[PDB]
Image (tube, each protein chain N blue to C red):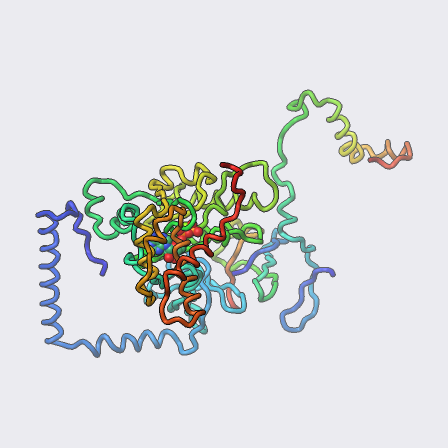
Length: 73
Length: 393
Length: 48
Ligand SMILES: Nc1ncnc2c1ncn2[C@@H]1O[C@H](COP(=O)(O)OP(=O)(O)OP(=O)(O)O)[C@@H](O)[C@H]1O
Ligand SMILES: [Mg+2]
């Protein structure tokens, strides 16, 4: 299932190419990186912490969760 | 043939005459000079052999592709039959008036450069909806309306006949006419008549025929119906039994009624919306009209609204003599005796009486129809009334 | 007509998908500059 390039007539694989994804999938990717700080949302102060701890914390400090011996959410 | 517009007052005047005399005189000078040249030299040989050069440029195995996007600049993207997409150059001899996306274009074999176009079928829907001449009859077979027929003639026929009247004063004709009244009273017939008598392409549709069993097909049908009506010059549309599609629009409803409302919105936009409707008229019929949507029958959508009463005393005599017209009757036919009764008879009821009497006359082998047969048939037809007698009265 | 799907490496090398014909890994003729071509834009290529 890999993606390789072949000679046009001898049909001999000649190089490895990046995997193929449907263009629709690729368009879903972020490029602009919006700019809205955690100050712009007020009144949801518990929820913001919940989500930040759930999603971002594991990605940076994975050592904590490994130490407690818990899989993160 | 792509002649100049006088754009004088456009109404019989001296300026319309002088701009008109001028074009005639120039055409006269041109014709004289052309005839002189043709006598001086046929040019048939020169005009020929240009066909030969063209046919040389377009090789024998010309390929029928399918244009898909004109870059607006004598280039195109033409798709071969298999499905490939090429980017070819449009040559100089193709009549560009005939180039629109989706047209079957005629490409070169080795170079696929566009070198012609072809005609297409004329029956997306044109055949299925157009009614041609009405087999029933012309305006002769309709009697008793007089005023209503006059209204329709002024609404739909007169703006085609003599545009000067409306044009002189700066007022456009009414938009649409809605025919409303008790069942069996002459709506569909009058539409048929004004169709078979006028000179446009008249299209007919039943409302229940816009209730489609796939989502988003009713709106497509209405959009097409109003799409092949500007392709065809002046045109008329008559959506009969509209009640089945346009209803009061009660919101507390579930099911396919939402699709009905959505097609109604599409129609409501087509009749009077963002764009200009071009040259088309809309007639409609509804036995029950109190139940239509206010936005469908509002002034700018349907200006004229026509009531259709039953025959009263004498139109009954007229209709009877219209349908009994072609049948040998005995000399004892007390027609008035059948008409005098105030039985609230309807026009379709009169036709039913005529046919039933004729049929039993056939049953009894008798070469002629007798009054006794007509009265018996009348009793038999009225037998289809029913209901609760004391109740309500 | 061909639909570019990827532009790999800084060096021009373009994977295009000709509709219903084939899928190739081709380069830029001299007329087009590298900035003009992006991923996902229809492009025209020659028959040789
Ligand atoms: N004044 C009339 N002159 C001639 N025929 C008439 C007249 N009134 C009714 N009819 C007859 O009525 C028959 C029914 O057709 P018609 O077009 O009149 O129906 P309609 O009024 O549109 O009916 P519906 O309300 O059900 O749509 C016609 O065949 C015609 O024979
Ligand atoms: Mg009717």
